Length: 91
Image: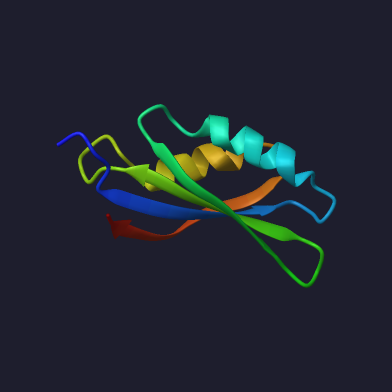
């Protein structure tokens, strides 16, 4: 087929308000495995001083692709409190 037919949006919550965001994204973007693609990075700041990051990761609906997998790789990065897969959709 050659394209991407799925998108999984992973929400990452930083450990605390003081976390440098630009650096976080840059680190997370390179932790994204080779076969996945990036479609969009969004910031959703919250009232308490923190700002959640939303990654729209591209993949395929075939063995070998696991959005929970990249969420986990995301959780290994420093200053990341947690990474979850909010939803997955066909594209």
